Image (cartoon, rainbow, N blue to C red):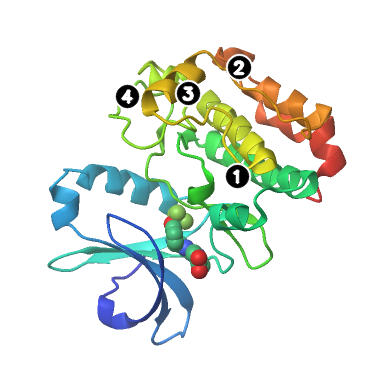
Amino acid sequence: KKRQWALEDFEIGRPLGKGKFGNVYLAREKQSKFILALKVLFKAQLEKAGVEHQLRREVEIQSHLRHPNILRLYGYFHDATRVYLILEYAPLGTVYRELQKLSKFDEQRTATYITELANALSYCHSKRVIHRDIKPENLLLGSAGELKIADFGWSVHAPSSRRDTLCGTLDYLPPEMIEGRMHDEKVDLWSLGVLCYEFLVGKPPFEANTYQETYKRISRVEFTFPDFVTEGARDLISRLLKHNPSQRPMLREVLEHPWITANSSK
Ligand SMILES: O=C(O)c1ccc(Nc2nccc(Nc3ccccc3OC(F)(F)F)n2)cc1
């Protein structure tokens, strides 16, 4: 930032969670007593998979973003064996844990999260950063219960054509990404529809038991709605889950959607 941290500057605390790169810890900076989170990546592990350059992207991108619905990255440092990310600490944990708790969210809490997400993504898109990995496990909650986009591990500059070896769940990836094609900001609009659906239903709309058939359901956009999903909600999700990226709405239209405005507290 201006100056260079070391492990000895921080008292480390409770393990927050993760993960196979290394874990995330609550920590406190000794001199200021500032409370934050410290993500410990293992180097040996980053190099037994040559991901060292992706971290530099994540770090570079996330550190330059200022938005109340995006998790701050303050800086980083390393020693012999590992790298440390100094992160804003989000006190209420992941959206996933919350979703697991409530099983599903009401329309008011979904619309509010979608709004918060939409604002954060709009900001991202103004810098032509595209996220590409929006999902409950990557979204944290602030002290006021506000959604924060947390993990920028897969974010990248737009437009992009990468055939990134897609290794985790397909559940949030749009057709143009699973088929390995070129893609832009509209990726995050598809993911926003997947998320909106998952928030209301409790499961992502293309969920399946194998990767191979999730792939099929996505590329053919086969989802159905349980009876309890309201018309307004169905309408927004159908607008978002469009095979053709150019037919997906702009974030502005998401924000101005009657189902959003009627239910959003934000
Ligand atoms: O369950 C809890 O007690 C809990 C309480 C507070 C926080 N808060 C928190 N603040 C900053 C970073 C961070 N990483 C993280 C932690 C666990 C899983 C995934 C993570 O990374 C992410 F968010 F990027 F995915 N977690 C997280 C969890």
Label annotation for residue 184: 3
Which mark is nearer the camera, 3 or 2? Answer: 2
Label located before the other in sequence (4 or 2)? 4
Look at label 3 and name its amino acid. Answer: Asp
Mark 3–mark 4 contact, CB under 8 Å?
Answer: no
**Residue 181 in the image: x percent, y percent?**
38, 15
Look at label 1 and name its amino acid. Answer: Ala
Label located before the other in sequence (2 or 1)? 1
Task: Name which residue lies at 14% across and 49% down.
Answer: 47
Residue 68 visible in the displayed image? no
Label 1 to label 3: alpha-carbon separation: 16 Å
Instruction: Determine which residue is flagged by label 1.
Output: 120
Q: Quadrant of the N terminus?
A: bottom left
Instruction: Determine which residue is flagged by label 4.
Output: 162
Label annotation for residue 242: 2
Label 2 to label 1: alpha-carbon separation: 22 Å
Query: In terms of depth relative to the viewer, which is nearer, 241 or 160?
Result: 241
- Looking at the picture, does residue 75 appear above or below residue 26? above
Badge 2: residue crowd in 10 Å (few <14, some 14–19, many ≥20)? some
Q: 50 left or right of 107? A: left
Label located before the other in sequence (3 or 4)? 4
> In the displayed image of the protein, which residue is found farthest to the right?
262
